[PDB]
Length: 284
Ligand SMILES: N#CSCCOc1ccc(Oc2ccccc2)cc1
Ligand SMILES: [Mg+2]
Image (cartoon, rainbow, N blue to C red; front, side):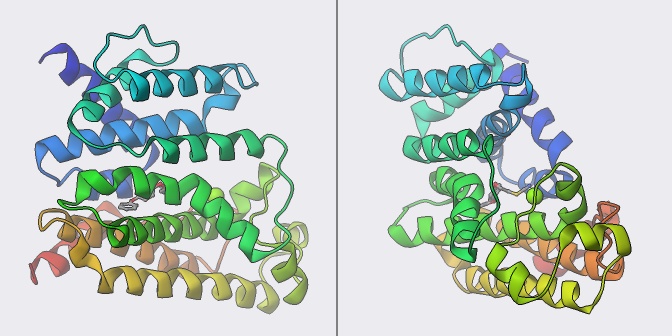
């Protein structure tokens, strides 16, 4: 194993530790493409977790500066200020693929904003957030997973990213609430007569289920529209991206099955993931 192999292996570790679902699917990609996905994912994870390093923006500022050095001098040697292993891997990717750097900056700006989080007034603000933390990631991944990127390719990837984010939110209501985060909009909470603190204390009720299902319907419709447009992606990536998406859709059924519980994180069994993969490959 070379030094760069070690860098990418560390990126893989970070990705698998954070999301088994995502890892399961994307580990099926060809070698060059899988490694690029690991590096991009890891950078994004590092940005997402940055604030809790010392409890301020110091590390996040360093990450941003590392990315800016890569963008402006992709072929110069850099002494990276943040996580060297991850930044060397990203630089290696950048030398071979067109990285949407403004997408990383959008993600970083979103993370900056999150330290003075206030609840979203409307669903438009919530969807803006889903773009910020997840749509941006889809945009960065676009050139890795497609051969000739058009505005359509980016559009579809962006939509998938945002659907996944919404599904994460739908899975993590209780956990987010404990961490003083509520992502459902105030508009929608008021309309459905829902109070998350109340529900966390007293269990689900029909108002909450209706509110939850309202958003779940959005995720599922977005999912189907992405499925209809799967051919913008390279032939190798299509089954993989379809797998990722299906595994996440199944997360919604896992929640319904646990009766929308706010007190544990539901999940799709590894064996169930293998089943979805079989069902999908059968038609590939
Ligand atoms: N965990 C979690 S929530 C994920 C948030 O960041 C993303 C977003 C999308 C994604 O897969 C995509 C593949 C192609 C295009 C767009 C997305 C992987 C990670
Ligand atoms: Mg969440």
